[PDB]
Image (cartoon, grey):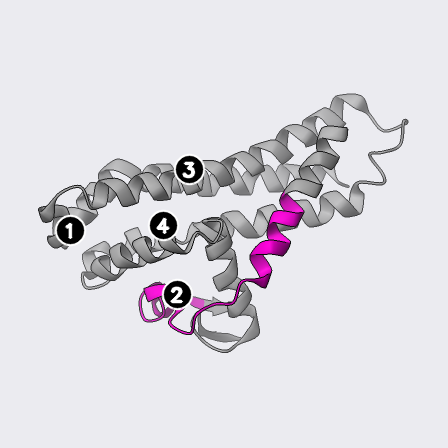
Amino acid sequence: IDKLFEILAREMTIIKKEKLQTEIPSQFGLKNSMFELLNVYKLQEKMNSSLAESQKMRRQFYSSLSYNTTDIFNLAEIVNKLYKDPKAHDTIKKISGGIRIQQGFEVALEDLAINMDKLKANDFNKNTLEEIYNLIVDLTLIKKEWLSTIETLIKSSNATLELQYNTEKLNDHIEQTYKDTMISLCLKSEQTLLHLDTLFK
């Protein structure tokens, strides 16, 4: 149960730091790429608008990559190459479940702190407190894996002049090597929440 507190203090501060960061107006290369492709709803604008709910939704993508601006630049570079080719627009969709992932992590954590008082009770089931911590970690872990994957991608997508140049193949590369991984990671994230969300109630 202290691990849980260590966790909350640890990630919830890391996010304070992340929120203070200002976006650069350019939205990191991604204004007219990822954030024009995608349409945030409720009740609908593009993800690049002034509209509040989207500016939050841009942060969450940045925070997915722990706001390492270099990575976000280096991913834009790639996304920008993929956005010329409709054939590879679905790859661009998979790359932005980093957002969905993150939202759930903020939400799980928002509730953790809330419900933290209830599972403090010496009375609360120890064989379920365990279930919860396990999920909690798994969330925090997926997060890691994701950033990990994004970087790894960035390395192999610029490993050869041909993979910097030919979009047809760049995308193949990514579909081949990472799309599944980004799919499943996006799923694991839902479903851990949903399970967790149950557990809180």
Residue at 40% of width from left, 38% of height from top?
Answer: 148
Q: Position of residue 170 (x, y in %)?
A: 17, 48
C-alpha gap between disc 1 and disc 4: 20 Å
Residue 112 lies, with reference to residue 96, above or below; the image says above
Query: 131 left or right of 64?
Result: right
Q: Which residue is mark 2?
A: 38
Between marks 3 and 2, how big is the CA–CA gap? Answer: 20 Å
Q: Residues within 10 Å of mark 3 (few under 14, many from 20)?
A: few
Residue 89 among magenta residues: no
Q: Amino acid at mark 4?
A: Lys
Amino acid bearing label 1: Gln
Q: Which residue is mark 3?
A: 184
Q: Which residue in the structure is indicated by mark 4?
A: 94
Choose mark 2 or mark 1, whichever is in front.
1
Q: Check disc 1 and report the residue beneath it.
A: 164
Please tell me which of labels 3 and 2 falls first in the chain: 2
| Quarter location, residue 25 | bottom left
